[PDB]
Structure formats: C-alpha cells, structure tokens
C-alpha cells in the first residue's frame, strides 16, 4: 500500500516460546511506546509523547485475546510451527567516527523470524554490558521483525567491537565486527 | 531447535494528503501468514487464507462489531492523526553534514536528522555531479533519527572546490560543506 | 488520548 504515512495502533505479538508478548505503537516505522507487560506500565519512546496517557491494561487484555486465538490456530493448523529465517546483521556508527569523541555503535538485526533473538556486544573477545540498550521488535510488512541494539562508546585506536547475534536461523552465533580505524 | 507458534495483530492506518485519504487495515497473522483482515476500503472482514475463514464468518455475523470497525477509520486513525500533527509530525532534527576522504572517494555523511525527506547533491565547482555518485539507502537508526552517506569518486585537479548540498525540512536554508585538496 | 484497536476472540 502507498501512503504518505503509516501507523500501527498497535503491533500486538504473542508466541508460545517463553511464552512472551509485546505491545507497541509505531508511526512511520518508529516505536512510539511499548507497554511493559510484567510491570503493567506504558513506557514512551519519544519525550514529546510523555504528555499522553495510555492505559496499560488495554495491552494486557489484547495480548490475552492473542493468546486465546493462538491456541485455537495451533490446533486448526495441525501444529504448523513457525519457520526460522536467516537474519541479516549490520553494524555501523550513529555519527562519523572521530577518536576521542563519544559515539554510539548500532547493530541492526533484520529479517527476524520468529521474534526470538539474543543480541550482545563483545570487545577484545569479552562481553560488554555497560552502555548497551535495544529497541523492541519492530514490525515489517512481510510480518518478520527487526531489532536494533546500541552500545555507547569513546572511539579509541586500540579498541574494536563485535555485535554477537544468536538466532535459530543461524548454525552458530553471528559476529559482525566494527573497527575505529 | 525449539518450536514456536506465533500470532500477530496489527491495527494499521494509512494516511495520504493529511486526512483527506485515510485507510484502515487490521491484520490477524498466524506465524507469518495473514489469515483474516478488515480493510476499511472493503467494509467487511475477509479471510485471507482458509485458516481465517471461521474468524471472518463469526466476526461478520456480529453487527455491533462491524459497526465499530467501520467507524474506526475515524475514531482511531483520523483521531490519532490529530495527535501526530502536534507531536511526531512536528519533530525536526537538523542534520549534521560532514565530508571525509575514503583518496579518490569523498564521503558526505548526513547524520541524525528527522523526518526522512532529504536531498543531498554533490557539486564540482558549480556543476552538479551525477555520474560517480553513489548513496547508501536511507538508514533508520531506530531512535527517531536517520542518516544517509553520499559518496563521490573524484579525480581532483588543482583549484577544484567540491561541495555537499543538503536540503531538509528542519533547515531554514540548505547546508553546504566544502572540501578542497 | 491515543486510540488503539482491539483484537477479537477467535470462535
Ligand atoms: C538466548 O539465550 C537464552 C539463555 O542462554 C537461551 O535460552 C535457552 O533456550 C534453550 C532452548 O529453548 C533451553 O533449553 C534453555 O534452558 C535456555 N536457557 C536458559 C538459561 O533459559 C535462548 O535459546 C537463546 N536464544 C536464541 C535464539 O539462541
Ligand atoms: C488534498 O486534500 C485537500 C483537502 O484537505 C484537497 O483540497 C480541497 O479540494 C476540494 C475539491 O475536491 C475543495 O472543495 C476544497 O476547498 C479543498 N480544500 C482545501 C483546504 O484546499 C486537495 O485537492 C487534495 N489534494 C490532492 C493532491 O489530493
């Protein structure tokens, strides 16, 4: 469909593995908010949107409808499971690299299905957790997902990084390297 | 390899020319197969695959549900659009424009801008360069900013002045960055 | 307030 703008009010996800769910709204491909289903609270992704209120119970009730519908379709499909796809991983920086100026590494994990993935960061072969964050699963029109992880850093001549991606569509974890040059 | 059964529900709105043309499409998806749909251009639930037939028939038989669905293009899509008009559609992040050699190849990095609409052109003296220019796709950072990198292959002669011209809705006047050897 | 769309229960 062709449109000046496209929104999802919202993207609802529920899956048997876990199990787990996700509730978000999207506008022109970006995440407006998610509902933390465990804490039952709306978490706005854009500071200008904090002026609004969204009842988290709407999300919890909707996910329960998805959970019920899924159980029905598992039976009717004769337990037709999801097919694992091969995700595509790319690492790049938010801004041009200048040594000694703060930056952010971005790891895009695209063509994700099913939406179950572990994205971590490595430096000199050891895991890095400080300064790491990630988006929710963001929707795609072919009904796969993408997800983006971030690592804040101070670029330095001696220090390189890997984005590490575990997904059932991969024989072994995928490492995408980034060098400051 | 764990098995997974996945269900998605997407309540989508498509906008063209403000709210003059608005189309609502809600999609129920089993794994990656959309099985049943409500398209406001159609006005009733329609099965997309055989697995969605029982839901479509049950949902179409409920006259109150159909009435609410047929009004949702206004109660949801056009309603939420008024909120986008004073939040997301007013978001302006001015691009940062940098030129760095990579040196017969110049990289014009245009980073951290919102919204997506942008135009980047390379000039040699006062002549626009089209051959020898190659650009990345528009890159979505996931944090409500974009970037794009526009490269120019050159054979630079003495006195030549190369400029990267960037126009964007956030800019009162276009940004021009010069590079000289 | 921002309006969401409900999913409906399968028969
Ligand atoms: C991400 O990491 C978690 C934790 O290591 C993995 O969870 C394991 O999943 C297997 C298969 O379902 C279970 O048998 C294990 O008990 C789980 N471990 C733990 C500690 O819970 C998960 O599989 C990983 N995801 C991917 C896509 O590789
Ligand atoms: C975009 O939509 C606007 C409405 O917001 C259209 O402008 C209207 O056009 C009708 C004719 O059908 C006039 O009677 C109105 O007075 C117009 N309103 C305004 C505010 O100008 C416009 O034609 C549409 N443009 C496109 C390209 O579809």
Image (tube, rainbow, N blue to C red):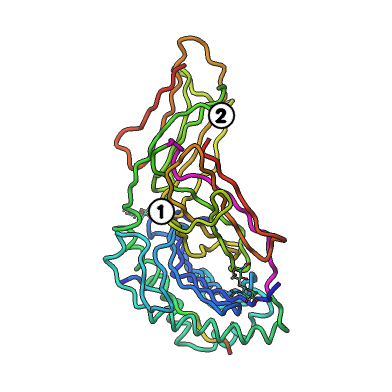
* Whether the residue under disc 2 has CB within 8 Å of ligand 2: no
Task: State yes or no: residue A91 in magenta.
Answer: yes
Q: What residue lies at 57% left-to-right and 88% top-to-bottom?
A: B58
Label 1, label 2: how many angstroms apart (C-alpha)?
27 Å
* Residue under label 2: B133
Across and down, in percent, residue A71 comes to 61, 86
Of residues A29 and A94, which is closer to you in this image? A94
* Whether the residue under disc 1 has CB within 8 Å of ligand 2: no
Mark 1 or 2: the one toward you: 1
Q: Which residues are magenta?
A: A82-99
* Residue under label 1: B144
Q: Locate the N terminus of chain A by quadrant.
A: bottom right
Circle 2 marks a residue in which chain? B
Circle 1 marks a residue in which chain? B
Across and down, in percent, residue A139 comes to 53, 63
Task: State yes or no: residue A146 in magenta.
Answer: no
């Amino acid at each position: 469909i062709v449109a000046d703008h496209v929104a999802s009010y919202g993207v609802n996800l529920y899956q048997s593995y876990g199990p787990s769910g996700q509730y978000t709204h999207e506008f022109d491909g970006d995440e407006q908010f998610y509902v933390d289903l465990g804490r039952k609270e709306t978490v706005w992704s854009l500071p200008v949107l904090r002026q609004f209120r969204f009842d988290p119970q709407f999300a919890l009730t909707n996910i329960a409808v998805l959970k019920h519908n899924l159980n029905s379709l598992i039976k009717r499909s004769n337990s037709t499971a999801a097919t694992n796809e091969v995700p595509e991983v790319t690492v790049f920086s938010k801004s041009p690299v200048t040594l000694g100026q703060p930056n952010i590494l971005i790891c895009l994990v695209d063509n994700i299905f099913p939406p179950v993935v572990n994205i971590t960061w490595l430096s000199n072969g050891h895991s890095v957790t400080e300064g790491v964050s990630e988006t929710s699963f963001l929707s795609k029109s072919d009904h796969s997902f993408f997800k983006i992880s971030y690592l804040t850093l101070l670029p330095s001549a001696e220090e390189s990084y890997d984005c590490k991606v575990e997904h059932w569509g991969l024989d072994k974890p995928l490492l995408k390297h980034w060098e400051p040059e | 390899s764990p098995e997974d059964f996945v269900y998605q529900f997407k309540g989508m709105c498509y906008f063209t020319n403000g709210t003059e043309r608005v189309r609502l499409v809600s999609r129920s998806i089993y794994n990656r197969e959309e099985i049943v749909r409500f398209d406001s251009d159609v006005g009733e639930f329609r099965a997309v695959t055989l697995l969605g037939l029982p839901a479509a028939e049950y949902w179409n038989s409920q006259k109150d549900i159909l009435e609410r669905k047929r009004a949702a293009v206004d109660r949801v899509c056009r309603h939420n659009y008024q909120l986008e008009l004073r939040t997301t559609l007013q978001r302006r992040v001015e691009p940062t424009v940098t030129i760095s050699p990579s040196h017969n190849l110049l990289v014009c990095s245009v980073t951290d801008f919102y919204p997506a609409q942008i135009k980047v052109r390379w000039f040699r003296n006062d002549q626009e360069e089209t051959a020898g220019v190659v650009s990345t796709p528009l890159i979505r950072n996931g944090d409500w900013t974009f970037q794009i990198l526009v490269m120019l292959e050159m054979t630079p002669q003495r006195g030549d002045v190369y400029t990267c011209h960037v126009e964007h809705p956030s800019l009162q006047s276009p940004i021009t960055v010069e590079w000289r050897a | 307030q921002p309006m969401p769309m409900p999913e409906l229960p399968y028969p």
